[PDB]
Length: 63
Length: 57
Image 1 (cartoon, rainbow over the protein chains, first blue to last red):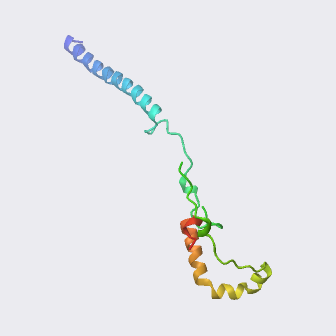
Image 2 (cartoon, chains in turn green, yellow):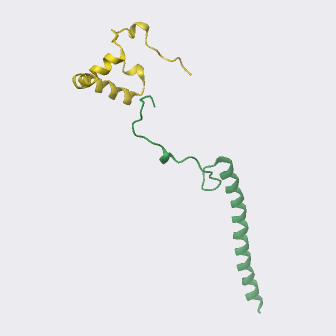
Image 3 (tube, rainbow over the protein chains, first blue to last red):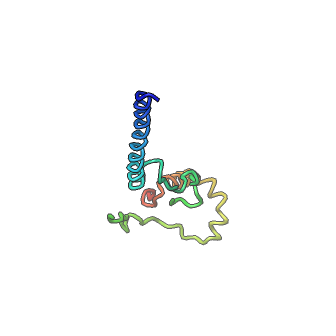
């Protein structure tokens, strides 16, 4: 292989590896914030579904 | 937490219906027909407010 093919193939590898390395670091930051604040799709633990609640008038009034 | 607002003892004085349960049972059917209007308004207030202090009148 000529020096140019190896040279410019190397840059293609470096760009791919650098992009992945950046995304790896961002993911650890997103995971840290999502777990600390619980305001994202991850670390979202279920809560009772409000649609299980009965809203019709009950036998007694005060409720 | 705040103080629970309560009506005064004078806000609760009314002439009570001092008859026994067998008397009410006997008159119940005619009572339900004749006194439906104020009775149903009170129970509407009662299931809407969900608070006995809001339906005293």
